[PDB]
Image (tube, coloured by chain):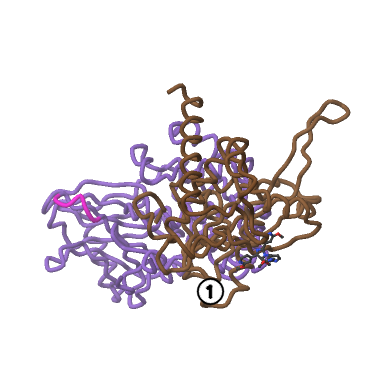
Chain colours: A brown, B purple
Amino acid sequence: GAMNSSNYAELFNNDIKLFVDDTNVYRVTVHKTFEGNVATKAINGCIFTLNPKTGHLFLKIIHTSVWAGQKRLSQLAKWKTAEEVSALVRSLPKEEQPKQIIVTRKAMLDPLEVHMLDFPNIAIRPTELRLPFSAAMSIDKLSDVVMKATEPQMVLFNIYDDWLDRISSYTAFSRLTLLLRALKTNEESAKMILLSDPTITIKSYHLWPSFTDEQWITIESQMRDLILTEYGRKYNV
Amino acid sequence: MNTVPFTSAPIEVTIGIDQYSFNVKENQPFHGIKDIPIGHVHVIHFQHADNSSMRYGYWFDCRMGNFYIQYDPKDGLYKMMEERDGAKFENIVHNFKERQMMVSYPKIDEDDTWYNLTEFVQMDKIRKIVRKDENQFSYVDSSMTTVQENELSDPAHSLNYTVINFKSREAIRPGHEMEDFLDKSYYLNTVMLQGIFKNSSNYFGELQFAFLNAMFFGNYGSSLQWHAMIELICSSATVPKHMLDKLDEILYYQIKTLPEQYSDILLNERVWNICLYSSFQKNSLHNTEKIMENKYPELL
Ligand SMILES: COc1cc(CN2[C@H](c3ccnc(OC)c3)N[C@@H](c3ccnc(OC)c3)[C@@H]2c2ccnc(OC)c2)ccn1
């Protein structure tokens, strides 16, 4: 069925599953033409395909060249996403292929289903959750690799860094979603919080700072405060 | 003009012949239906006064033999049977007409409704959808399930309609996933028309038969099939021009003949709004569009 707060711990069982987020596949700036009309200019994008168990972020970089000469690009983007996800599954050994793929937007269901017709025993699921994966381009290292790409690419990131050595998948996923929710609501403050202390550094192959266990607690607290404040402002509560 | 005699009418029943129906009382002197137009298939159907559930009936073609109705008190229904002895049959029919105990198939001369609803329907094709080859006529009822329905349970009593599934390998070419899903022309034209149906007349016949089983028996799986065959054409960018014009006429008479107070379950909101207003063929169904708007503007 659909994935929600009731069946939330299912992500951390031993059935391989992937989340697929397509929000950042087709990315445009909007600008004025000489004649005073409006045109879009695309920039590089990415499919965010995440194993919420291991931390693997199968980042497929979508180069602007894939849109050249194509119409209805927001619709194509969903099919391109499904084509790339299906290709990934095919490339993987049988015992690494997911048993479920959970899409973060329901418009991806039919394109993925159609592209996965050859995998009848992979379940394609929507979710009721409001996951903050769109904020992935607020992670500096991920944004950098996408913007610098000159061709289609697939880069495998560990979005949990070394966290699983000390915490569970459940706790790692909650930390990730809390960081991304913060980056999504107020990128500037969220980033100030993460880099305030110049003595804390980021490991060359890692996305986030080297916090000790107690520093993570302080950081996680600072991120919650941010997310609540922003909400008061949003609504007037 | 041919005749379908009835042995007796032991139970109170609403009898239908094509788009006509008559009420017959328990043990009323009733011995059948005369003046049935030759050259078309026909359906004779039944709803018992005591059980508004299970409408049932027989598809038949009088060119294919002499057929009569007889109530079976064991199985509890009006059964169609064939009389092999021609002279026994002529004589039963003559005696019953002489005593004027038969109703007359009540065709208005100006009226082409039944022809328009059955134009492409062949008895030989009905018999392959309803498999029971010891009889020349075909039984259908409210509860019978279709083959596709049975995949997602008794096969002898299934409606063997052609399986249509837009999210299947049969419908989607490897490498053409987006193309074939948004433009079903290859599935319509190559897979179904050329491959399976051979020609559009057989396609139109199954579509027409599906609609009629849905209308007369409230057969839900026939209604799914009808809508499915409509949506496959409407969702193809490339349809022969003769097919679109004929489809418009077909749907027009189906929509015209539907009972007005049945449009809630028999008509699928999503298929019709898509076909009439979004699909490639949104502008090729002028007649069907006009009658739907003036008669069911709520659905849309
Ligand atoms: C196809 O995948 C890759 C991956 C990368 C290279 N990565 C990256 C990565 C991380 C950060 N910045 C990047 O900015 C291009 C790329 N992910 C690494 C990684 C981490 C954990 N588990 C991993 O996999 C389970 C992978 C790995 C790498 C490269 C360089 N140094 C490493 O040090 C030990 C490790 C580059 C190219 N192709």
Give coordinates of residue A169: x percent, y percent: 45, 60
Q: Is mark 1 on a helix, strand or loop?
A: helix
The residue lying toward the viewer, choosing from B70 and A64, is: A64
Q: Is residue B17 left or right of residue B294?
A: left
Q: Is residue B291 left or right of residue B241?
A: left
**Which residue lies under the disc numbered 1?**
A96
Residue type at mark 1: give it.
Glu
Q: Which chain carries label 1?
A: A
Q: Give the range drawn in magenta.
A: B50-54
In the image, farthest residue toward the right? A34
Counting other residues with Cα less than 10 Å from the Cα at mark 1, is it few (<14), some (14-19), or many (20 or more)? Answer: few
Query: Residue B300 magenta-drawn?
Result: no
Task: Locate residue B148: give its quadrant.
Answer: bottom left
Give coordinates of residue B87: x percent, y percent: 28, 73
Query: Residue B53 magenta-drawn?
Result: yes
The residue lying toward the viewer, choosing from A207 and A30, is: A207
Q: How many marks?
A: 1
In the rendered image, the quadrant that contains the N terminus of chain B is bottom left
The residue lying toward the viewer, choosing from A123 and B292, is: A123
Q: Would you say the magenta stretch is mainly helix, strand or loop?
A: loop
The residue lying toward the viewer, choosing from A113 and B253, is: A113
